Every structure is written in structure tokens, then in C-alpha cells.
Length: 303
Picture 1 (cartoon, one colour):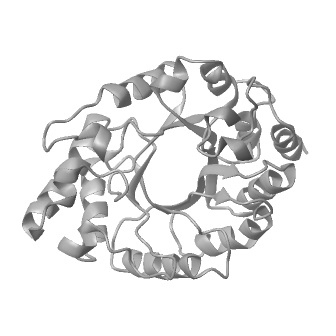
Picture 2: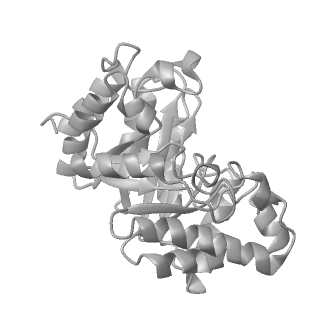
């Protein structure tokens, strides 16, 4: 990695990684691979480890895309993140149609154990449960909550811990960017209770899809998230409408201010590949050149 890469510079400040989400298609097009090799220390799969990619029909697993990402990361000395193991948004129809509690519990356990066992020892962080909370802090009414009940979250983490004790297990959600927002306060209290009951939640991953100007509020929200007492917290899938250096520097400084925040992962590399490309929210432009926000992060990390 470059000496002045954001990953090398955030390591020198005591953190673990500066990461990025990617997948096979990106790694063979443009300059994505060259930038990841030089500038980032951890890679995450955008879609290749989601449920509809890995188990499109029950017990008929497909790992071709995820294997590609894992192999590439190992050949290039990058840490690997994985997920999401339990998430309502990318579910095959055969899962969402299950109505029996014992059936769905076993299907969920098998999905978790099969993915984690395949990459046992190679994955630093697994997103086990994603987007479980409504905006008011109540639990989102997914098929898992409807059929298994709220015990599905404890069961998921206990199953994951048993499959690979080397991985850090995370719950993840979005709109945890304001200290006064109900979802931010609700998840802290719920995670405290689960850990008090012995559930092995190692971390909270904050998605951090920001509108312009919302970076300032992370300075207070991230300390709040860390007050839940998990071993780790992180910023995940970071992007910012407008990509103002002020917002990006604020998010980095929040990470630096929180001892338990281990790193930051951005949603992608180049603006045109973003889901909201018209807001140019990433750190590299269409020609794969660093944007002012990138140079501002580098400068903030140097001194």
C-alpha cells in the first residue's frame, strides 16, 4: 500500500483499516483493483455474499462470486468482511414464504453455518443481522420476526459464534447518524440488554449513508453507539451526497475520537458506479482520480 494511502495513515493513528465494498465485476474493470491495492486495507462484497446470491434455492449454494472476492483479497493481502447473513432486503422467495417456526429457524442456522464454515478463519468481520430496527426503535417486522419471534437475533449470533470463533460478529443498521434520533438510542439499549443476556454481539456497524451536512452529527452519534459496550464499532458503506470534505473529515474525526471504532469502510470507489451517482458521493471521480474529499482525509490523518 502507498505510504500516503488512507489505510496506511489510519493504521498509523491506531486504527485497523480503511476499507471499501467491491466485487468481481468491479475488480476486472477500470482502475478499481489498482486503487484498492494501493489505498485500502479491507474489502467487503457488495452482493456476492447476500442470501439471494449464495442460496438462490434451499441447500443449493453458489459461492463462485464470493470465492473470487476472498481469493483476490488473500492474494493482495487485504482484510475481508462478509455479510449480510440475515437480512430481509435480498431474500429469495423460498425463504420469505416459510411459515413454520422450526423450519425457518433451521434454514436460518444452516445458511449462517454454511457460509461461515466455508471461509472459516479468513473473515475478520461478519455482518450477522442487518436492518432489524424500525425508525422508531421497534423491531422491524420481517419474516424472521414474524415466524421465529425476537429470539431470532440471539439465535443468529449464537449460531455464528459457534461456526467461527475467530470472526467478529456485527449487527448493522442505517440512520444511526444522529445522537437524538430514536433508532440510534433504541439500538444502544437493545444491544446492551442482549449482551447482558450473553448474546455474542461483537460490534455495531453504522451504514452511514449521509445527506449533505450530516457529518457533523456523527461526532456525537458514534460515541453514543460505542456506549453500548460492544468490543467494536465501525462505519460501514459510507457515502455522502455532494462528497464535501467537511462531511468526510467529520466522519473520520469521529472515528479517531472513539477508541472502540476500529475503522471505516466506504460504499465504493468511483462516483459513476454509485447507486446515487448523480450526487457524486464517493472519493474518486469518473476518471478514478482522487477528489478533494480524499485529499482532505489524507491531510487530516497526516497531522
